[PDB]
Amino acid sequence: SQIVLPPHLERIREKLAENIHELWVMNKIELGWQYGPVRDDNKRQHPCLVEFSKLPEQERNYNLQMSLETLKTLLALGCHVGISDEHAEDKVKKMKLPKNYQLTSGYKPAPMDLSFIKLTPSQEAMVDKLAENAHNVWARDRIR
Ligand SMILES: Nc1ncnc2c1ncn2[C@@H]1O[C@H](COP(=O)(O)OP(=O)(O)OP(=O)(O)O)[C@@H](O)[C@H]1O
Image (cartoon, rainbow, N blue to C red; front, side):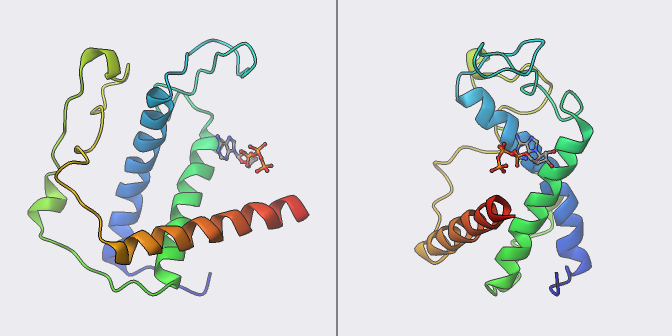
């Protein structure tokens, strides 16, 4: 909470929050899950697969806030803020997946394919630390 976002990282915060609900629904569709009227895992139907508005707005807001907390954790571990270029921010590419893996909504099936992006071990350990901190947050939630 003591960490405050710089305004530029803050545009990127809301924009990547939209990117995060996109990634969440895309993980949901990568799981090969089914969409239905009722929110039951046992009968294997959930209407939380298509877009953010189809979700409960409070659930989407909590998704946004946990993405915000995840990037605040990224800041807390002390990552130096870096940006490639302004074009890579104004215009992001839209990879197309086949129709089978195409989302029912109008969003791009994924931001861009994992082949061209190789993530360095410096941030690989960074993600591990994110994993421990998220596990600790869930654990204190269970303790509460
Ligand atoms: N799919 C979701 N992922 C994360 N948070 C969610 C999700 N759906 C609802 N929430 C929000 O999270 C809170 C409780 O749901 P949550 O998913 O955290 O619980 P859970 O999966 O039953 O497990 P735990 O209580 O251990 O977190 C509420 O504020 C709720 O609005």
